[PDB]
Image (spheres, coloured by chain):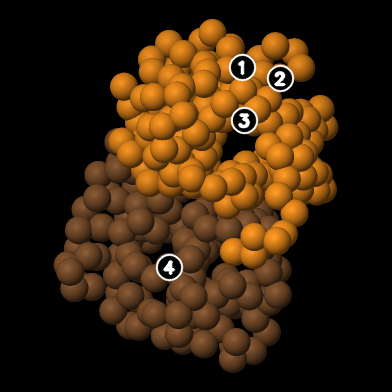
Chain colours: A brown, B orange
Amino acid sequence: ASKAELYATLAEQARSLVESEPDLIANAANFSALVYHSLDRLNWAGFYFFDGTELVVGPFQGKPACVRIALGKGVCGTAAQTRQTQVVRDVHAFPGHIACDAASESEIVVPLVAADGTLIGVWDVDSPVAARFDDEDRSGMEALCRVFVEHAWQKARD
Amino acid sequence: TLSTDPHASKAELYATLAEQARSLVESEPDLIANAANFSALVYHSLDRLNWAGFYFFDGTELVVGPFQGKPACVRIALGKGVCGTAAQTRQTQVVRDVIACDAASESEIVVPLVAADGTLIGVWDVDSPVAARFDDEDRSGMEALCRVFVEHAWQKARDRA
């Protein structure tokens, strides 16, 4: 299946899954499981949630990794501080990449921002192969995260 | 790989994993982070597993928390299925041959999680695609792992409130 097909399907599956469920933790864990087992050549997929000061890991699929990430530090901290998606083809060349993120060869991080500008956290996907993610994954991952923010986080906050 | 390495028994392996679990959660205050990391640690330390994670009691029924594996059940009523049976009976369930959730599961162990004051926290659920993957040594080992999580993550956070 092409990337365009996979992300179109994932977007509707994700919306179906989280709209029918109030609990944010359930929705974050099921979302991580859905994406992780639908895309090949991944070794990590999951959430970090902002605690008012820094990122703190939430539900994820993969091996134990970073537990806390300061804003500005590494790919995830850079995404949270700049509020810009990070598409990294070679994590070992990303300036300031952090030790607990060493299992990843390439990475995509989408910042999650509430409608009122509050930093929610980041969505982080890692691969053990080089240049796994391109700008179509940028489009596709961001569409999945918009579903999550609108129909899981924004709902529970209200 | 490397057959000449030391080959530990189930008791020793679960004891080593309990110390790792203790070290992983001891100093982190956030309960959801510890639950996510604990699920990841156990799932990747034991072989022949296809699911490992938490369902948390919301006061009425079980609601899935952090887990490793494909999407499974989201909500489970008390008394329904292996996990709901564990939560209601407050008894550990060991199933050698598998209603719901992870379809590929052939054997399963569910450990109820109960607070110091008797509150039902939820359950810890692990599945294998192999028949009779879990025996009474796995039963004892999983219960010891869950004591670490309840003591050094859940009860720790509750007592600070």
User: Are labels 1 and 4 on one chain?
Assistant: no
Q: Quadrant of residue A50?
A: bottom right
C-alpha gap between disc 4 and disc 3:
30 Å
Q: Quadrant of the N terminus of chain B?
A: bottom right
Q: Secondary structure at mark 4?
A: loop
Whole-percent x, y for residue A136 in the image:
28, 79
Q: Check if mark 1 and mark 3 are on a common chain.
A: yes
Q: Is residue A85 above or below residue A146?
A: below
Q: Chain of mark 1?
A: B
Chain of the residue under the numbered disc 4 shown in the image: A
In terms of secondary structure, where does tag 3 sit?
helix
At label 3, counting other C-alpha atoms closer than 10 Å, the crowd grade (few under 14, some 14-19, many 20 or more) is some
Tags 1 and 2 on a common chain: yes
Residue highlighted by disc 2: B115
Judging depth in this view, the residue of A102 and B2 nearest the camera is B2
- Between circles 1 and 4, the one closer to the viewer is 4
Asked if marks 1 and 2 touch (Cβ < 8 Å), the reply is: yes
**Amino acid tagged 4:** Leu
The crowding category of the residue bearing disc 1, from other C-alpha atoms within 10 Å (few below 14, some 14 to 19, many at least 20), is some
Q: Which residue is mark 3?
A: B138
Disc 2 is attached to a residue of which chain? Answer: B
Furthest residue to the top? B89
Task: Identify which residue is drawn at 58% across, 52% down.
Answer: B44
Q: Which residue is mark 4?
A: A42
